[PDB]
Length: 90
Image (cartoon, rainbow, N blue to C red; front, side, top):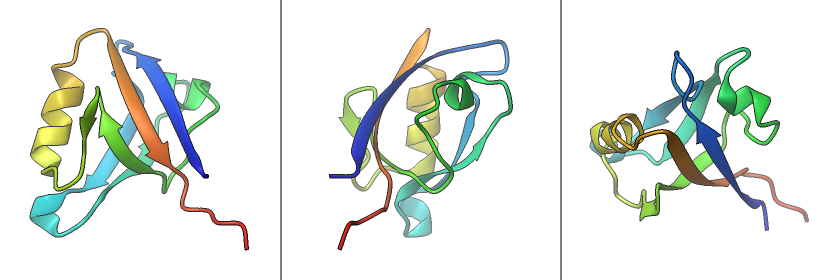
């Protein structure tokens, strides 16, 4: 249980995060960067390395990068994200 959700409201510079990966690069989808002062960083919830499992209700399983970007940009005033931290308690 290292799963969490976040809902961000667009600012003039977007939601304030970058992603890397996608199915065309034989990769999952991760948070690459968090823009200083932006909605993602202000949320206090996200970090670099977190895996994006769902965007706006749609699973990211086998999602192209291009498709994830398109969903977020074209999603209107907010983005809803379901994430995984990549931390495990042993």
